[PDB]
Image 1 (cartoon, rainbow, N blue to C red):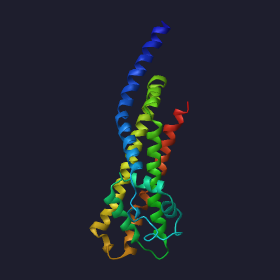
Image 2 (image 1 turned 45 degrees about the vertical axis):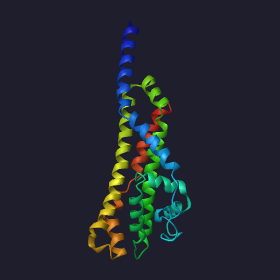
Image 3 (image 1 turned 90 degrees about the horizontal axis):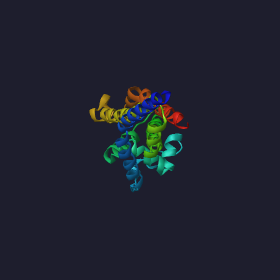
Image 4 (image 1 turned 90 degrees about the vertical axis):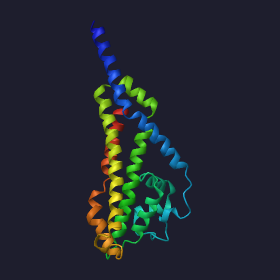
Amino acid sequence: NEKEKIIKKIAQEFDENEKLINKIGPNIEMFAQTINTDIQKIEPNDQFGINKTLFTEKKDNNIDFMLKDNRLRRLFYSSLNYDENKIKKLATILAQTSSSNDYHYTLIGLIFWTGFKIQEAFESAVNILTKDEQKRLIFNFRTKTVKEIQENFEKLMQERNSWIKIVDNIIGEYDKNTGGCKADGKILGEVIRVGYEHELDSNKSMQILNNIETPLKT
């Protein structure tokens, strides 16, 4: 009954893994469907204002990636739950920022970058955690690993939500007219830089992803 002992433990690990997975499984299925629905959307011809008429080509690499690639623009739109009004409003707000040293272009770029990188990490995690993979986790992994993965997934969900809140706060400065930024594109750039540049962080997302990926290659 070394056998009986091991069998009881295995049955308990299946039971507890399943509860951990059941916490994220319904969500992942919804997110996968939502992602597919966003991918199928027709982008408007104006690209919600994220085009070369409003953001000059060749000022920032991350701006240029957005101007050039509709799939990176789709990621950025999905990073904001494809809220069209919000996307258009942000784009309008950004296209009127200004500065002396052109740094506003770097800030614009890091905003676009942060959004498409967070959504890319999020969608990769969603795409990796298929039903088959979830079943693989339940039946073949120690409960400690399954817990780390489930909680790292919830962490990634939160990163994404904190990113949305940053954008909401940036729009909020403009709506409040902080420092009279509505009338001055330089004031607006500085409002956004000082309030929010340090807040931008797609590195954390991508590390959380890597920590979900590395146990899975087992």
